[PDB]
Length: 56
Image 1 (cartoon, rainbow, N blue to C red):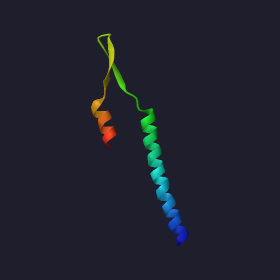
Image 2 (image 1 turned 180 degrees about the vertical axis):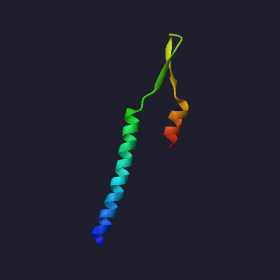
Image 3 (image 1 turned 180 degrees about the horizontal axis):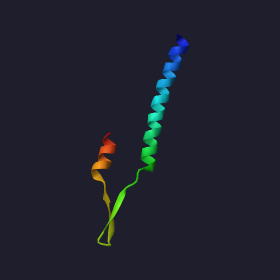
Image 4 (image 1 turned 120 degrees about the vertical axis):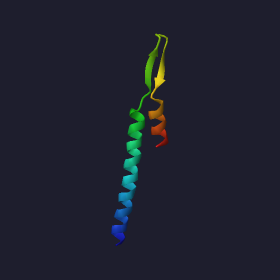
């Protein structure tokens, strides 16, 4: 019973750690979408997607 509860706690901790690792992977592979603007600058695109990801 105690060992089963310890294993359940470890499983929950592993689930939380896996979710944090997934978030880390998303936020170190995520990059800004740059679009050229009349051969002067590269402006950022993807505002709704970036804001939705941050909010989620």
